[PDB]
Amino acid sequence: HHHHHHMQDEMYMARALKLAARGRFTTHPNPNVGCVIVKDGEIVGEGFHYRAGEPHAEVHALRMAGDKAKGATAYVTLEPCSHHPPCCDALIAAGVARVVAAMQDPNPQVAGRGLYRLQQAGIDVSHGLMMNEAEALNKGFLKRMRTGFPWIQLKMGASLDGRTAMASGESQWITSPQARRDVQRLRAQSHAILTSSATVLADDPALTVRWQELSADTQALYPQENLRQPLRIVIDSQNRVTPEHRIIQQQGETLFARTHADERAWPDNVRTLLVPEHNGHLDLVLLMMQLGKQQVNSIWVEAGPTLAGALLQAGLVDELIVYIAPKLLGSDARGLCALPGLEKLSQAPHFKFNEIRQVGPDVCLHLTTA
Amino acid sequence: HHHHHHMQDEMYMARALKLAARGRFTTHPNPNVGCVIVKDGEIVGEGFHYRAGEPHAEVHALRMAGDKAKGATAYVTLEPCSHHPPCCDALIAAGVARVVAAMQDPNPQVAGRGLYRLQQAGIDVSHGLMMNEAEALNKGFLKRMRTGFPWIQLKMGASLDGRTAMASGESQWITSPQARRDVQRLRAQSHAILTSSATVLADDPALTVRWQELSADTQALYPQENLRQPLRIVIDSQNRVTPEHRIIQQQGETLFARTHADERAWPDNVRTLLVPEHNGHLDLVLLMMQLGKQQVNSIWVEAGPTLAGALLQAGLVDELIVYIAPKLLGSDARGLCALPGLEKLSQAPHFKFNEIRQVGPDVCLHLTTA
Ligand SMILES: [Zn+2]
Ligand SMILES: [Zn+2]
Ligand SMILES: [Zn+2]
Ligand SMILES: [Zn+2]
């Protein structure tokens, strides 16, 4: 009816969340999950999910616990499987007497089914402890489940007066090496990286994660041999990128969003997703919906002003990450985003400053769509 | 040869600096000075300079101390007068046995003259304790003394993509009321406020300090009846501002920088400063030098992109104060500063981010010319 181990429960669930976060570079498309199993006031098993196709966090914790799971309390950051050999029946089979879940399964057709199954077989169950943190841990995955739309981070880098290139086109190092290394850490956590054909034609980028540019913090949780390249997505409405561009010659897969199928021979890692047309342009809303159906949780956008403005105007951006260099390029220089049709101040895209921070000599601004 | 009251000395000099800072809205053109007089380990007199033409900080402290100054230590944030009835002879006349000065007089022809005079008449003197803080307290005044150039703060307000108006000219509230109130607090500390004829023609501003827009912090140190309007300086090369504009109808003085004398009748508070011509434009470097000679310590610049870029390109800006609103106005909108001739990235004005802070829904960025 009520107990007095709330502080202990909070300590173990916080540990389970710490463990879950250790999967964030590699679990895609699965969510990050952690599990801690406590017997007589000491932790006898822990685990987290690391890669799709590997065991769930509860299974790792039960393997550690062994016989010690009999009579133990399990803390899990997400409701255990109900039919996936499922984690619910593994927890019961091990003799767990109590289960605490941070949050219920986000799919409404199966939400609570696991907890009920444990309750049925005599387990004391509850859910909600540190729900808010469990939500934050899988922000992008959860938004995709509940809306069908992947989480879209739009990255911008510009001068103090909002400029991304001189009028001459010269863009060589507005922002700092530190900013580039910071982008690499955020890239490594994204399910996919997305760009436009115009960016690929103008820049010939690789759009990969370089493990050597990662901070010693993230390099400690990310062994080099487990490096996961985010899926590289290229919007190419008119099939102008060639099979000789750097992007499709890196490790990992590359997906081209196309109007119609390309006729050339491409490397094995390159796939085509056919998106329908809206007026003369490839339909951005439909592209995102199809990517959501393909279980793409989060997308890091590296493109120019044209795609940045198009995504903004389609209402598809969830957050802006803006790197500002302490430089003025002047009013003839190129701007941040093209917003065709915008004429009145009150129609302008509006945001909220969440976090601002120094990044080398630059500053980084995190905004959402308020 | 050495002592053991360094901590006590630091405590009293820090109090003297706290007192000095209470003059910062009103002492112009004089520097902020504080004085603390300690007898037998208790403070018997304190003072700070408040307005030009009023007594110096040492005189206020000696008046408080009275007979208790006999045998006392005086802490002063700036070296006492040597011939201005001077503070040096007032300190000696009161029986002070020891004087500690944060810094020497910044004029090299009189630096140290006061301390020597005290030493001559038997006073133990030293200088340098919290010099760095004493310097910071009168940053703008000191730069004007040592270079002839007033301290120039250039204010900018723009959207996230660096825009100051829609293409239509609509500029109504990019930045927030909080940003405007923040500008008022910084304005109130400036010796002068400077603008361009184009700004006055386009905006018809008053360019005054409104006491009602000040934070309860600053309103506590700034009694309403002591309000000092910063000198309003208007650069008008071709005498286009009329005597009917709002700016010359506010309280306090207004100075017009002109190529030749205006022929119309102006209110009593309006004066003309004649600046020579460089090519077809009024000479900005010469204008600043003449203002320095007129003892103008610090200048808060409220103008458009044209004067902002001109001051930047003349190398006259000491710091930028940039208010950024969480809005995107798009690439057809008006920029922050006009930098004619700038084509190569390496020639762009470069800066260092010192301080970044939230100001209501906006952010404020402080930069210097690194
Ligand atoms: Zn109780
Ligand atoms: Zn499971
Ligand atoms: Zn000693
Ligand atoms: Zn004096």
Image (spheres, coloured by chain):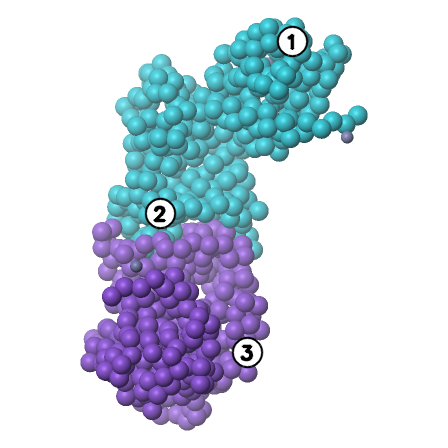
Chain colours: A purple, B cyan
Tell me if residue B341 comes above or below residue B63 in the rendering.
below
What whole-number distance in Å separates the C-alpha atoms at marks 2 and 3? 40 Å
Q: Position of residue B279 (x, y in %)?
A: 50, 36
In the rendered image, which residue does mark 2 sit on? B362
Mark 2, mark 3: which one is toward the viewer?
A: 3
Do the residues at discs 1 and 3 belong to one chain?
Answer: no
> Tag 3, which chain?
A
* Nearer to me, B367 or A306: B367
Write the residue at 24% across / 60% down.
A341
Residue nearest the viewer, comparing B135 with B10: B10
Name the side, left or right, on which A193 lies relative to A115. right
Judged by depth in the image, the label closer to the viewer, 1 or 3, is: 1
Towards the viewer: B196 or A254: A254
Q: Residue at label 3?
A: A223
Q: Residues within 10 Å of mark 3 (few under 14, many from 20)?
A: few
Which residue matches tag 1?
A: B70
Element on which disc 3 rests: loop
Query: The disc numbered 1 marks a residue on which chain?
Result: B
Could you tell me the amino acid type at mark 2? Answer: Asp
Q: Looking at the image, which residue is at 38% across and 51% down? A: B162
Callout 2–callout 3 Cβ contact below 8 Å: no
Q: Chain of mark 2?
A: B
Query: What amino acid is found at the position of numbered circle 3 in the picture?
Result: Pro
Helix, strand, or loop for circle 2? strand
Query: Residue visible at 34% across and 68% down?
Result: A134
Q: Nearer the viewer, mark 1 or mark 2?
A: 1
